[PDB]
Amino acid sequence: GRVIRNQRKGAGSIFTSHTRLRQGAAKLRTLDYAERHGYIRGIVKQIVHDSGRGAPLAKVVFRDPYKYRLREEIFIANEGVHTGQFIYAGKKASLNVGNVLPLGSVPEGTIVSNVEEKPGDRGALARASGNYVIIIGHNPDENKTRVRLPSGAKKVISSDARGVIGVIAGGGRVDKPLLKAGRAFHKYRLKRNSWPKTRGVAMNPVDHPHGGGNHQHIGKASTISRGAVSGQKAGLIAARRTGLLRGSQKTQ
Amino acid sequence: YATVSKTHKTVSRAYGGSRCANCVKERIIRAFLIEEQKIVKKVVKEQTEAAK
Amino acid sequence: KALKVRTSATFRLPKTLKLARAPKYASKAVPHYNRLDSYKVIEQPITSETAMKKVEDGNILVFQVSMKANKYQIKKAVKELYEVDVLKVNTLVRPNGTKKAYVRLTADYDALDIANRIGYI
Amino acid sequence: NPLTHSTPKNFGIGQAVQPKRNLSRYVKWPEYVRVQRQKKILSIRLKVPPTIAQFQYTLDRNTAAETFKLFNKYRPETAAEKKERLTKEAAAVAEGKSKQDASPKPYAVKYGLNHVVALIENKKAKLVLIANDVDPIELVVFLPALCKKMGVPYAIVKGKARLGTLVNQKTSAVAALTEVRAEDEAALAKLVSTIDANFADKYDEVKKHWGGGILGNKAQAKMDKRAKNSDSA
RNA sequence: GAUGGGGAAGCUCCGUUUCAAAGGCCUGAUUUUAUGCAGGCCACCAUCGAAAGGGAAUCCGGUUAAGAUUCCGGAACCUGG
RNA sequence: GCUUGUGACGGCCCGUGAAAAUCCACAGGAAGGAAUAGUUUUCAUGCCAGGUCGUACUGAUAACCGCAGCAGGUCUCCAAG
RNA sequence: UUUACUUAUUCAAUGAAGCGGAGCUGGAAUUCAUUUUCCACGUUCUAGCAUUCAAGGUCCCAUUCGGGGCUGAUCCGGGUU
């Protein structure tokens, strides 16, 4: 009967919509002949800050070619542009600063925005692709593209996307310690809650399968197997290494 | 607004609703700038595919 | 036998025809009787000191309505009698079983001269 | 007149509003429409069953014309012109005491499709036709076999609705003649040599081979264009 | 918390638009036809859901054994037909 | 002096300050139109109509919720010298 | 392991939005007799501007302030990006 606080997401209450503060999504509108190989132009004016974190959002509203309507669509903005600057991204034209081109019509060094990973389709039924323009070099070989990130993974996919060049002031926010503390509730009153990460040498005594009793010491390995039991998964999963990464790089 | 007469809000004028201050002036000044450059891209810039 | 012109919205709902929808007989032959009449709405006028005050201070009559009524079933009831117009109808709520009502008149008719003529004194 | 110009007009796609064009598929198709277009195919898309392979073959309008007109003179009387006739023979058959005596012979054309028994064991089958739509798929794979074994001249035709009008119904079947008059005697034996030389000679050869090679759609707009560059670019 | 889908022997639950044939109006030919065939448009298309929030409109004074911004007297405004 | 309300700023934003209906305005100008007569139903003036339900006292150190005439718990408005 | 053609399953949008092959045509690249191949097919300095069966031609009830084809926007495919 006494469960652990890893098996909670099955009530639909304290895990539901908790983000009044925000507005809309970020996925683009209807795709046509324009928003792909040929000619695609974007806009950015009211750079309203992204609610919940540190990012900009723009009121990218396109005059619908199919019908006289200008539905307000809050999309992701970028840093470097002022209050109003149209995108100059033409496949049959050229390239400048802050443009939107597929991952095939551009050479190495192309950090676009995130929207989709599939050859376009207004939010591909998937998403296991890139997080946006954030991409270095590509691959001239056919329509394939080999991306790479310092996270430690590889991926080979297509070379078509609707991401625009631009940056977001996020670097430094996590590099600068939460000095003036008082952050946990309003911290992750954002979308849900996942910041209690939470201890007790005697949190649940006549139990602790890990190891505790009456003294600060564990017993069993906190490395719970992935395919073994879904009733003991409390702590590390599928361990391999453990060390200390120093600041001095200069490696191979 | 509907309770009061029409002659208490916009009694005349024209370009004055969603824009004001100096936006009423900018909607004509900048317009004349580009339209005068349209002629160039209709006879002068169309001399590329003239000598086939 | 070629390209049918459909340059509009998707032809969804068909174009039905309104047939002569008329019954061959009455739904229940004899319709329900009228539950509204002048000789059923009013009942027994309450004779008290509180009632007399609410008569000569605004030209209002005092009776006793049944239950379900509005500002017309009482108004039309008076007009059906001796043809008397009503300026304002007052309907109250009596949470016990019965109910009361007030009937206002015009500046032409008199409340005291119509009270001893309708029935009571 | 003096303001005569030329060249097509251009809208900036994002700018302006475009009007509806020649909508063909835009007016989205109904539910079972996307189903029926993939339902009744059989001999169009992929391969065909050797037991049939006759739905792709049709009859010319030069022979079928004389065939339909031949069955025009042979048809039972309708319900509107038969029930009233019973009152006319009241003083000739009923009160006349003459059961099937003072009456002309009703030369009716033969019929029957999925219910044929007495027309095989008694050898009373001549001209045999095949239905068009045929909803029961299981009731068509043994129709030519009911004529090939007995040597009955079967004719692979398409249609049974118009022939249902000369039978006082809606759908028809075969149309053989066992007791035909001398008026259309030469107009019946002439069609025998035609059917036997265009249908009876093609059964064993058709049974062996499967049947296919039919072009599809966009599929042949890339597959055939690939072999062209693979052999001689 | 439904219809149109998708499990189960029955009693039902979740989701709220996740393959639509969902809704039927302005005008032309028609006051006295309670409306049958063709163009040009609009993507909203079960409901319920706050007596501290949201919100076009009325206050003061006097009388009675009790209670009003409701009746009486005086002074005004808005919406729909 | 204190209390309440409003306009114009700064500081705070590692944690970034809901949703909907009605009314009004601007851009755009497609239909229908006048000399003993056309064109607004928007101002002024005048006339008519607008249901049902809810409704008082009290609301707490003699009135609700703890067998009871209990010293417990119990939201909100104006806040004197 | 295995390229194309797959009447069965699932499938984001769905107001099937301007698509692929083929097909009236340029330019770039060099020669074997011609188009047997590869980029073409409405915005790209500025919240200044943009729509109403597109501004223009031919064919009709006649001199009408409107309306009805084709071209503009040719097909196949009905598996539209």
Image (cartoon, coloured by chain):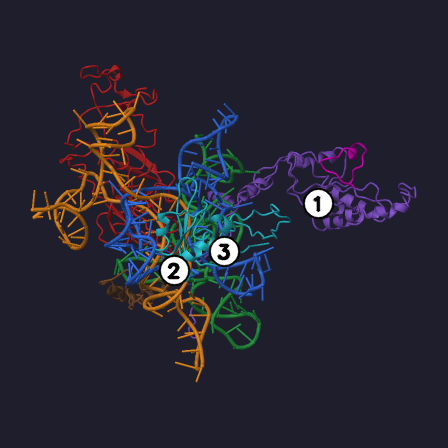
Chain colours: A red, B brown, C cyan, D purple, E blue, F orange, G green
- Foreground label between 1 and 2: 1
Query: Which kind of residue does numbered mark 3 sit on?
Result: Leu
First along the sequence among labels 1 and 2: 2
What label does residue D11 carry, if any? 2
Count of numbered tags: 3
Residue at 83% x, 48% y is D85
Q: Determine which residue is flagged by label 3.
A: C81
The boundaries of the magenta stretch are D110-126
Q: Determine which residue is flagged by label 1.
A: D170
Judge from the rendering whether residue A48 lies leftward or rightward of residue D134; answer left or right: left
Query: Which kind of residue does numbered mark 1 sit on?
Result: Lys
Residue at 28% x, 34% y is A192
Residues marked 1 and 2, same chain:
yes
Rendered location of residue F22, percent (x, y): 36, 55
- Foreground label between 2 and 3: 3
Splitting the image into 4 quarters, where does residue D139 fall? Answer: top right
Rendered location of residue D121, percent (x, y): 79, 31
Rendered location of residue A32, percent (x, y): 39, 50
Q: Residue furthest front?
A: C121
Q: Nearer the viewer, residue A77 or E64?
A: E64
In 3D space, how far apart are the residues under numbered discs 1 and 3 (Cα atoms)?
73 Å
Residue at 36% x, 63% y is B49
Q: Nearer the viewer, residue D12 or A142?
A: D12
| Quadrant of the snapshot with the C terminus of chain A | top left
In 3D space, how far apart are the residues under numbered discs 2 and 3 (Cα atoms)?
76 Å
Query: Which kind of residue does numbered mark 2 sit on?
Result: Phe
